[PDB]
Image (cartoon, rainbow over the protein chains, first blue to last red):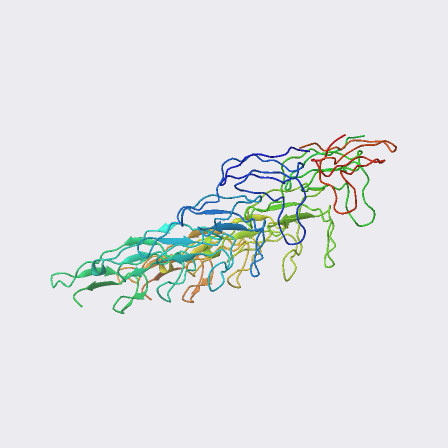
Length: 254
Length: 254
Length: 51
């Protein structure tokens, strides 16, 4: 049922064979095994399936522009005996090992990285529970990423990156419409659909928050000015004074 | 009555045979058995039925985009001995076992998820009596789903998801048309067609409740205002005062 | 280098195969082995010589 593949094949190039003949026993998940190699394909078996592949790489161009794929877990160690054709895998520069037969759902993502005010990352869990350092994740909820580098492009789909809000003290303050049961990332106060005030200078929008609008104060250290305000919910102002809706006050150099 | 199917067939591909020849005795519900497999289909029997199939899979692409089907329970354990062609099944990634002969009612549903205020799930029982953990459902009534994860798309047809209502305190409160003998899902009072008021902030319409309108309050902490009211049923107000229909009172900074 | 010799063959009849592939070790002088037999010649190896 086939011919001797005694063909010349170049060193970085790829070729898929014995896809038709039997595969291994036990947990050794070598299915129909194949080879990417330098030499002439001398073929000891004619029954073997022949798949015409000229150009292919296993090259991860430095750490930038890296790759992912369907796990083809053929080699293992004394610690990680991973599920082969059940899981999906992600790759860095540290993988210049040659290609396999059971690979699907893959491309080449460039590892984008961002730091502090620069930008943030709005990850979630597409099906993940506990894939990252030092503890465990709960359902399909969402995390914040602020500071230096990047991470694994796996088991999380990021909502987006967020270009944060920037606040120049006295002239500015930030409004933040809480969106879920959202606990305040900056204090104990929280309620869905509610409104927020940022008194800190140039800070970031936590995943649950939302930059509504940036609101500039009216300057009233002036003996020649006072503010006319209408309390809109029952509360205490910045200066801690009991206030009921509709009530009207004027604020002035206190 | 047929030919030797000695044909080459790829590892994840599927083929249907012996659909014409006799089936098993006793509870072993193997009918005309078939095989999805890696190797060459050597067929020791010519009488066999040949169902021409190139591309197929048992691929449940991670937990998302998963699949269900008409049951085919050939392998069982000690804890489970199932009816194979009466029932109907639902499947996740945790089942990459091959295909069968009795497959009829199936597709590729992505197990959509929603959590907290975000959205709700208006589940009903299409035929079901007790399909879910730690107890037993009464006929084809309706539940709600609120918080973290998803579940089994099986014995329950969902009415819809429900993008909930949202109320901002003193400015707002909700109206809810109770539609069944509906017991109040936030209190004790109840009656069909009746009218409700939501006094909590940003919440969710339970299954029997219906979002009518959200009603904003008139600001009357004003010394220059009072509200003219007309009691439409015999009752006691927010402030717990005896009222009768027709009756008119005015409400002012109390 | 050849085809699956899945052919029908009669009981007293004869056929010569695996003439091309390797032969045995030691004093067991089976070279390119063959078979005369009753059944259908299912051939697990395609490289086999067909006579």
